Length: 15
Image (cartoon, rainbow, N blue to C red; front, side, top):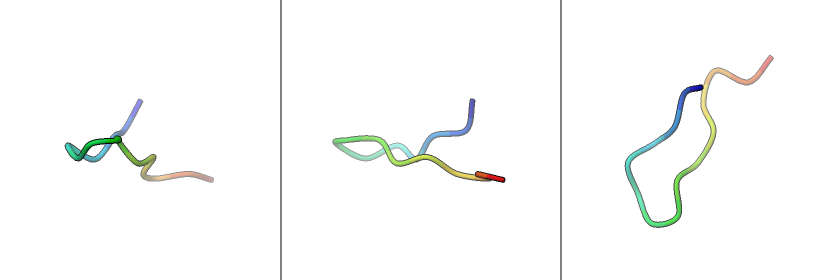
């Protein structure tokens, strides 16, 4: 799925 590229990754385009 969509994830930001940080430590830690964050979800994106969550419905």
